[PDB]
Image (cartoon, rainbow over the protein chains, first blue to last red):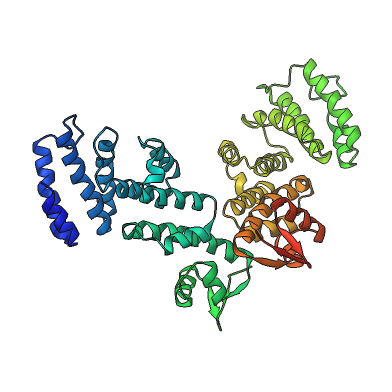
Amino acid sequence: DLNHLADLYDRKDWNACKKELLKLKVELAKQNLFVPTSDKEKASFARNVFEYGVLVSIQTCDIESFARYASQVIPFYHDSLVPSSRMGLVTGLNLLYLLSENRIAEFHTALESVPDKSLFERDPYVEWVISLEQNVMEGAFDKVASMIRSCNFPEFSYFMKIVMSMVRNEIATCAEKVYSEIPLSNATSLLYLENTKETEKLAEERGWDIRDGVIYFPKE
Amino acid sequence: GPLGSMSTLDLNHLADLYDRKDWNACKKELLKLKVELAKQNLFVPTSDKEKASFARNVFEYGVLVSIQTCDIESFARYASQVIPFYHDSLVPSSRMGLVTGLNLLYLLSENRIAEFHTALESVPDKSLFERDPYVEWVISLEQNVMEGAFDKVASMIRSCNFPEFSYFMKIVMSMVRNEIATCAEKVYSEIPLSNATSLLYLENTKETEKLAEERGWDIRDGVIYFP
């Protein structure tokens, strides 16, 4: 059963989790359970293995494995099993993945494909990601930044940082064109960075010169 | 002449009228010439290069006269007629670079960016991209537009040495201006009205007020406040 995997996961023993996932996947292969089956007991077990795979993959920033497990788990959801306690988080993670890769059409297709639409308000993870996507698309970057700063879902950290980097590049790209200079403090606010040293790092990355606390944007 | 042994009909009078900038006379001459093209079955390109060149030349003058008289419908019509003559083996006229550039500039001005690039892929002699001043300038313009290089676009347009491109200059500037304004909205909370006019490459304080209204900005005490 999955009690032991749950324990390993709870202790954040990711290396043991991966070894247990291998053991369980070998069992799935022996029983022909990689693809969903009408036998709900066995389908649920397989689904649950792949859910832990999604979670262990994000915890170890293994995005290749994440995307493989995500593709394996979602087909189990598009049938009639009792959702596990992980379903909202996994659904949320998959949506946020698509957002982080700017796969916006695929994101909205994924929402359309969600059997029960009430999920969008009932489940806090899915609700949060839907709101983040709306705020990004509307260019409400204050709200994006506030949502990402105050996010209470640790599992979203990896992808949220990618989203925030995309927003920050877009702001940075506008700024370097419509300013000739800006003080470091103002730029730190503008870019939703935490402090001016963070801004100094971004300035170096982008080729901006800083002199006496003022950023000068490359021109003519 | 180009149409027939004893014919007195050729392009010399149109070429005179064009250099005189007598655009109304040019239009009347173009209609005369097109009537004769119809009588001779020369609207459609023919393997007879003498005749095809004559018909092509009429349509090229049509392109040029149409843009001089601010007439985009006629311009687009004539452009659609002339380009098929280019996709065969005539010796290019002195107008071919300018016409090709105008067609490209038109597609850019309408944000028909896919068609812009298809049109470049269609140009038989791709050395034209570097050799011809008109085509080279438009290619550079479109590149700077795509990359969002606002100040380069503005500077190219401000120093353009090709009067025949004048029609499209403010149109392309408005495309870029939109983008600048979207940027300014994102990264400013306020700016003096006068600094906004300069940032946006606008002509005066009043045009900025209209743009303000159009985009929903507020102005007070000579200052713009962004939503």
